[PDB]
Image: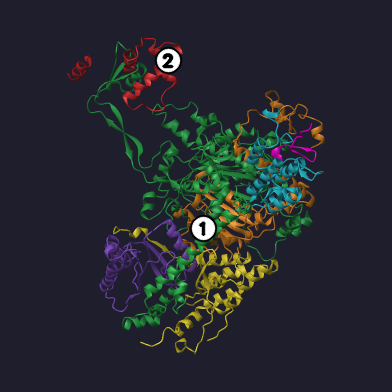
């Protein structure tokens, strides 16, 4: 739920209470199976934030170091 | 022992005869199915005389290994999982239809067909000879039609 | 030899040569096995000409070939000349004068029938039973079967009886099977422009004629009903070849931490204590869960099982198509759906179209339900014992549906509305007969005048496995080893019988007072003239069959010199 | 009214799914074949009842054979024609109209290229 | 009168030890032991069951005096449908009714070879093919279950019932049944085509405020409503003088 | 094509003539009653042969019960079953303690081709004009035809006229002096 908000905010620009709406819309549309790809889970969060978009009425490298620090 | 006695054949007419006379017969089938199992139960429940018994086994007269395996299962004591029999007749009518094959067409099929229709028939007679002989059976020839 | 190129047989024979039927050659060959020619063989090899003189006909190849050519030519000229004189007619004499001269073929459609029983002229009726019988019987105490239905591997009572008694379906067979199995769906409206009224392939939505249903579907219909390989789609994925189980292991070195909710992390710490660390991630509010060395883990693994075949309801059966609401479908255990559908189909078989018509003839308190189950609700049982154990989402009243008497409850709550008796039998593999006993008795005591009788059980993963453990069911791996197709693995009284084949479904019948049946004017399919249950003796093997039921033949022969007037109807009738 | 309720059999009110194949064929002839002029008042109405009798054959036959109404001209003696059909398929006198044939019948009533049928076959939305 | 009918017609053998249950069951309709034509075996296809069941059926025939040479013809429908534990007896009870009313005895089509053991049971006949007979008089459904749960049922042909009733009454009956069949053929093809076969009842025949009044009047019965046309209990038929008069 | 097919476990053995015989007979029986087999059909003779081929002290008590319990009165078909039945019961009594025999009674046939008036080639198998018994077939064989040049008895059958009568004949060993070889 941590990663799913940092995606909703990075790629779809959603603050604290606006990503609360996108999670609540995804709760009514919950998959009847676990999503396979992380890209399938990203694509799911996409369409869920646009069903929130027209229900609220709103429209729409450090990562290299991150891989190394993990190692250390 | 009778090979080639599938439905609608000279085989199956000879088989009905044998059963009607009270013979104990092993029939080979190549296409061993429910459909075929059901055929023979029908045939037996019609012509199966007192003292008769029909045994259907799947078989491929083209396999050396099947020829050997079959007539071994025939001679082997019931205890050892066999039939415990000793053949009095062999009717090796098993075959494959070769048509439209002339001299220069003789190939994989015909060479295989020749095996079923000659070489393995020899092998089969040879097999029951060894069995009888290995048992001192000198006064019970099997007739080969 | 002619048998299943004989066209020239008559011709070759026209030369004093004989051709033979197979029965003839077989007779000839068999004649070489006669003692006489057998001993001949033993003296020195015998050679038998069983070739009816063909030897003598010269240039046989070419002669043969000629006959064939002359035939084939005579055929092809004769057919070519006729096809041309026939076109010359359509030219000279118009194709509209010949068009009103062809006849119209009529093609059959399926008229499925309820197949009620036949009532003979009373003259013939009174010839069956003794004339003394008239009015001898209190018809208020003759238990009679008024309707029946089933849901099972072979469809309904109609299609199953057809397969059992005949071995192939009629037109009404396929059309009904295709319908229950979902292959065809009814349509009435416009089909791409023109109007249509009839069957439609439900996948393609194209029209289908009754006379075609067989060619189009039966091949597949047959493949997907009866005793066949277990289709995991029909059982939430139960796959006898890869059977899911978990094993316990102790973690030998600290697992790597994973993120989790606060509520969830606490449920872990509650469980593991010294053997797990959970810590709040101050930024998100959520916790990290780290399983230390010493902790207990469940690691999934798979098991290959022996029972690969069951008698399953035809693939595509759907309580939705019998007309059952989605809400019920959800709420209920599969077995209740079987039961519901048959109670409906059984009332139909009895010509009771609205259950409340009973309440025209009877009081609310005199319609009962004595249907029973061996296990019943095996599916809700799992959700309760296993699906809960995994914290999987499962209903809050799966307990309801697990009970055996709740099937009868939904029947009464959705359909019947009776305040009659409700005695529910558990009789393992005989709950159904015991049910009839219980039914019969309840009517003979005045407690009910109509009641529902029958049995039902479902096939599920844990059921089949435990039977396999009792060594009760047939071993499919072994059946295959013996050359046995699935349709062949249930063979009672056979030399090779090897264990029983498991199945699923339900079957109920409606029973009634003979007197009431006559008055209502429903069909009468038979008389339940006796029904008994009996225990065996002292033992220690529960799954064992016995001879308790032999007691239904118990009569005392210590004195049988002279005839008992009691047996004599003529006598009894006078006394009455 | 000039359009009777079709599924009324000898004064007896009833519905279309509670008539037998005979009752319908006889009701058809009754309302479309004008007795006094020994004539089908409209050729489409003769065509109609033919299509219906043909259907009767289709339903009740067991195997495939050929129609007893090869040409609808045979309907010009309606009574005789009807008896021919139902003699062959006697069962059709005793059974109510198959549920699926009701849809059919009502569909023919909606066929353009046919003089509007002289009755009301159904109480429903298009009753006006 | 009903009790006299009972004493001499229905239950004459109850208190008799020389008349077995099975005997008298058939005997009340003028049927002999030999009349039980078909035995619907449980036929579990297990070695344990099939032998036992044959033996036990054999003995109940032997004890009661089944004519030497008249075996019961056994069906084994588990061969086609399998074994659904609980639903077993019912399926066999159906096939039994269908056998009675058709005269057809289906064949154990999976009987490649009858177990030689079973030859001793000279009162049982194991057919591998269907026999279309000129009549079946009575079938015997027997079934066995875990926990020594044994059970038998005897189903007698319907036409023996009509013997015990007046001709005028029988004729009146045939009338009603005929009308039902027509109206049921109606219903069935409706619900098949339109998936209307099951139609959940959304109300009881009694209003909630009438529920108790119905449970307590034994003569309360349903009548077609005017408005709805469906079957309800009326205030005027509950505890009525008219329903004591007409009863 | 040379792959293996035989395994011992796939063998199926058929034993129970004792049971198929009661069935064989209880079938001929309903079939005559229902008139599928009429007293002309050769099938009743064939099937007689197969029933006799399985005489038990037990098969007898079977036919005995079922035959003696038929109501001759019930119909013309019922008398037939009963008469044939009794005849069959008699024969079985004799063939008890007697070797089973292969005897083909089928009606002998020959080839017949016919081409339509519209070029439709059709093949039938017709009964041979001058051949009716397998007996007559052997005689036909021994005479040969004119085409075999250089070298290198009338026993009227009740055959397709009265099956029950022929059935009564079955148990009786034919004595012949005029050996067919001498024809």
- Are both tags, 2 and 1, on one chain? no
**Residue C379 position within the rendered picture, expressed as x and y whole percent measured from the top left:** 47, 35
Q: CA distance from mark 2 to mark 1?
A: 71 Å
What is chain B's hue in the picture? purple
* x, y percent for residue C225: 48, 46
What residue did someone put label 1 on? E54
Colour given to chain C in the rendered image: green
The answer to which quarter of the image holds residue C446 is top right
Q: Main secondary structure of the magenta part?
A: loop
Residue that label 2 marks: A52
The chain identifier of the residue carrying mark 1 reads: E
Left or right of C195 on screen, residue C77 = left
- The chain painted red is A
Chain shaded orange: E
Numbered range of the magenta stretch: D1-19
Chain D: drawing colour = cyan
Nearer the observer, C194 or C521? C194
The quarter of the displayed image where residue C447 is located: top right
């Amino acid at each position: 739920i941590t990663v799913a908000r940092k995606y909703l905010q990075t790629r779809w620009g959603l603050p604290s209470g606006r990503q609360d709406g996108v999670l609540l819309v995804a709760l009514s549309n919950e998959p009847a199976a676990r999503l396979g790809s992380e890209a399938d889970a990203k694509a799911f969060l996409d369409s869920m934030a646009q069903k929130y978009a027209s229900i609220v009425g709103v429209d729409l490298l450090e990562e290299i170091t991150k891989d190394h620090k993990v190692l250390a | 022992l009778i090979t080639g006695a599938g439905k609608g054949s000279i085989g199956a007419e000879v088989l009905q005869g044998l059963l009607q006379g009270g013979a104990k017969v092993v029939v080979t089938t190549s296409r061993f199915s429910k459909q075929v199992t059901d055929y023979y139960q029908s045939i037996y429940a019609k012509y199966g005389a007192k003292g008769s018994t029909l045994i259907v086994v799947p078989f491929n007269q083209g396999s050396k290994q099947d020829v050997e395996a079959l007539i071994e299962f025939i001679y082997d004591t019931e205890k050892n999982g066999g039939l415990g029999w000793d053949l009095d007749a062999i009717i090796p009518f098993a075959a494959i239809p070769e048509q439209g094959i002339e001299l220069e067409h003789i190939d994989s099929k015909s060479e295989f067909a020749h095996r079923i229709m000659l070489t393995n028939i020899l092998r089969m007679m040879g097999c029951v000879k060894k069995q009888k002989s290995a048992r001192g059976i000198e006064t019970r020839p099997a007739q080969v039609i | 030899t002619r048998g299943t190129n004989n066209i020239i047989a008559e011709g070759i024979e026209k030369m004093g040569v004989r051709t033979f039927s197979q029965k003839e050659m077989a007779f000839n060959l068999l004649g070489l096995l006669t003692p006489e020619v057998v001993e001949l063989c033993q003296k020195s090899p015998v050679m038998a000409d069983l070739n009816g003189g063909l030897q003598f006909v010269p240039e046989l190849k070419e002669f043969t070939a000629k006959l064939r050519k002359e035939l084939v030519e005579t055929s092809e000229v004769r057919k070519a000349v006729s096809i041309e004189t026939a076109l010359e007619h359509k030219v000279v004499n118009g194709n509209s004068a010949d068009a009103a001269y062809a006849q119209v073929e009529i093609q059959p459609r399926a008229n499925i029938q309820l197949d009620f029983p036949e009532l003979k002229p009373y003259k013939q009726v009174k010839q069956i039973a003794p004339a003394e019988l008239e009015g001898l019987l209190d018809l208020e105490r003759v238990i009679v079967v008024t309707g029946f239905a089933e849901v099972g591997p072979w469809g309904s009572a109609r299609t199953r009886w057809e397969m059992e008694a005949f071995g192939e379906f009629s037109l009404e067979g396929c059309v009904e099977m295709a319908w229950i199995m979902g292959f065809i769906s009814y349509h009435n409206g416009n089909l791409k422009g023109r109007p249509y009224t009839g069957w439609v392939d439900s996948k393609t939505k194209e029209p289908v004629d009754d006379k075609d249903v067989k060619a189009k579907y039966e091949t597949s219909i047959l493949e997907h009903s009866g005793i066949r390989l277990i289709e995991p789609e029909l059982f939430n994925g139960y796959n006898p070849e890869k059977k899911e189980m978990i094993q316990e292991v102790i973690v030998e070195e600290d697992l790597e931490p994973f993120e989790a909710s606060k509520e969830t992390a606490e449920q872990f710490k509650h469980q593991h204590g010294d053997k797990v660390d959970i810590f709040e991630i101050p930024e998100t509010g959520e916790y990290s869960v780290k399983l230390l060395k010493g902790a207990t883990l469940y690691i999934p693994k798979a098991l290959r099982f022996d029972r690969l075949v069951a008698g399953q309801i035809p693939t595509g059966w759907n309580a939705k198509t019998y007309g059952i609401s989605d809400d019920i479908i959800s709420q209920v255990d599969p077995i209740t759906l079987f039961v519901l559908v048959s109670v409906v189909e059984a009332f139909i078989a009895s010509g009771i179209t609205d259950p409340y018509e009973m309440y025209k003839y009877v009081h609310v308190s005199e319609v009962g339900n004595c249907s029973g189950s061996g296990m019943g609700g095996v599916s809700a049982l799992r959700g309760m014992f296993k699906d809960r154990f995994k914290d999987e989402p499962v209903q809050n009243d799966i307990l309801q549906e697990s009970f055996i008497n709740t099937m009868s409850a939904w029947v009464n709550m959705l359909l019947i509305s009776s305040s009659g008796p409700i005695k529910t039998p558990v009789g393992a593999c005989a709950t159904s007969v015991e049910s009839v006993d219980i039914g019969v008795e309840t009517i003979l005591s005045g407690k009910a005048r109509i009641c529902i009788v029958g049995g039902y059980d479902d096939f599920q993963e844990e059921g089949s496995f435990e039977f396999g453990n009792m060594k009760a069911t047939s071993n499919t791996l072994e059946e295959f080893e013996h050359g046995r197709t699935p349709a062949e693995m249930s063979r009672p009284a056979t030399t090779t019988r090897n264990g029983f084949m498991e199945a699923q479904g339900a079957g109920i019948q409606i029973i009634m007072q003979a007197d009431l049946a006559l008055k209502m004017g429903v069909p009468i399919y038979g008389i339940v003239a006796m029904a008994a249950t009996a225990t065996d003796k002292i033992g220690r093997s529960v799954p064992a069959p016995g001879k308790g039921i032999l007691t239904t033949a118990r009569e005392h022969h210590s004195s049988v010199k002279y005839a008992s007037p009691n047996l004599n109807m003529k006598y009894r009738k006078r006394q009455l | 009214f000039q359009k009777p309720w079709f599924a009324t059999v000898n004064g007896q009110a009833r519905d279309l799914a509670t008539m037998t194949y005979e009752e319908v064929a006889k009701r058809l002839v009754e309302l479309m074949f004008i007795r006094s002029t020994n004539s089908w008042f409209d050729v489409t109405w003769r065509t109609f009842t033919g299509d219906f009798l043909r259907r009767v054959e289709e339903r009740f036959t067991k195997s495939k054979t050929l129609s007893l109404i090869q040409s609808y001209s045979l309907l010009d003696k309606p009574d005789e024609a009807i008896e021919k059909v139902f003699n062959a398929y006697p069962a059709a006198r005793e059974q109510f109209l198959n549920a699926q044939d009701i849809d059919h019948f009502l569909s023919m009533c909606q066929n353009p290229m046919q003089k509007p049928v002289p009755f009301v076959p159904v109480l429903d939305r298009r009753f006006e | 009168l009903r009790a006299a009918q009972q004493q001499w017609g229905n239950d004459f053998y109850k208190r008799d030890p020389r008349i077995a249950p099975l005997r008298g069951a058939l005997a009340t309709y003028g049927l002999t032991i030999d009349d039980l034509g078909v035995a619907s075996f449980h036929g579990t296809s297990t070695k344990a069951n099939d032998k036992n069941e044959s033996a036990t059926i054999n003995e109940m025939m032997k004890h009661l005096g089944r004519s030497e040479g008249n075996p019961v013809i056994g069906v084994f429908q588990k061969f086609l449908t399998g074994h659904p534990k609980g639903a077993a007896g019912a399926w066999m009870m159906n096939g039994a009714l269908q056998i009675l009313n058709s005269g057809i005895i289906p064949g154990n089509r999976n009987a490649d070879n009858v177990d030689k053991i079973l030859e001793q049971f000279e009162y049982v006949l194991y057919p591998s093919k269907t026999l279309k007979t000129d009549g079946v008089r009575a079938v015997s459904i027997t079934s066995f279950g875990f926990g020594q749960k044994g059970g038998q049922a005897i189903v007698v042909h319907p036409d023996y019932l009509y013997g015990a009733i007046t001709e005028d009454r029988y004729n009146e009956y045939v009338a009603k049944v005929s009308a039902r069949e027509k109206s049921a053929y109606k219903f069935f093809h409706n619900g098949m085509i339109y998936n209307k076969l099951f139609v959940s009842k959304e109300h009881a025949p009694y209003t909630d405020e009438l529920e108790e009044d119905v449970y307590l009047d034994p003569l309360a019965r349903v009548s077609k409503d005017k408005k709805s046309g469906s079957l309800t209990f009326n205030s005027k038929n509950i505890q009525s003088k008219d329903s004591y008069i007409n009863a | 094509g040379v792959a293996t097919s035989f395994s011992r476990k796939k063998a199926r053995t058929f034993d129970s003539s004792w049971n198929w015989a009661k069935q064989s007979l209880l079938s001929l029986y309903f079939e005559i009653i229902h008139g599928v087999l009429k007293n002309v059909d050769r099938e009743v003779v064939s099937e007689a042969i197969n029933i006799m081929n399985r005489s038990n002290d037990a098969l007898i008590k079977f036919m005995e019960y079922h035959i003696s319990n038929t109501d001759e009165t019930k119909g013309e078909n019922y008398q037939l079953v009963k008469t044939l039945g009794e005849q069959l019961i008699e024969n079985c009594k004799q063939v008890l303690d007697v070797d089973p025999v292969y005897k083909d009674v089928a009606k002998p046939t020959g080839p017949k081709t016919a081409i339509d008036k519209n070029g439709n080639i059709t093949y039938s198998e017709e009964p041979r004009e001058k051949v009716r018994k397998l007996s007559q077939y052997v005689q036909e064989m021994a005479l040969g035809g004119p085409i075999t040049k250089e070298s290198q008895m009338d026993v009227e059958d009740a055959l397709d006229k009265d099956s029950t009568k022929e059935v009564a004949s079955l148990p009786n060993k034919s004595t012949i002096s005029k050996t067919v070889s001498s024809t």
